Image (cartoon, rainbow over all chains, first blue to last red):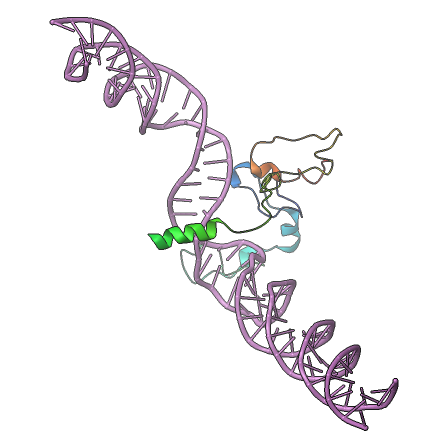
Length: 50
Length: 61
DNA sequence: GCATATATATGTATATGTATGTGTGTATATATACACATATATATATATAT
DNA sequence: ATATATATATATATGTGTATATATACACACATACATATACATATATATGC
């Protein structure tokens, strides 16, 4: 979609924008089932990732 | 009432550079061309939506 | 006729103290102005008539 | 000679769409600046001094 440039800073609304996980996530984040599970039970993501 | 009419007469007749022909040059949203106003092939783009303003400036003439 | 002296006035240059940021997004809510048509309604403009 | 019967295009309004915007708190700890003033040096000059 349209993400702006150096010259404009305000991103557009969600209604024109598609997104997906990048490969660089998979380069630096791995082994995520060992992530430290948060103390709140309905905090479904962990404390942080790897 | 006389005081408010006096302030209307006070800040009504003031200021300089009274050359009102363009209070704002084009529009804030408008992309003003460098050879705009003179004889060239100077082309205006009437797009729809300000969220289209991304990349318009970058690879235009 | 000429030394001179100092006085204050204006450059000037810095050093004060403020004043406005907006930063950069998060966060909270709200507002805006148009195109698509029939269905009433209303309100006031004209005729006439004795 | 104006009271009134009446007719007709004004005002929402419905939902769908399609797009805008806006006031604020948060806070450092600087960033840029907004003037700004202010005190002091020195120049010239002229009028005193001789």
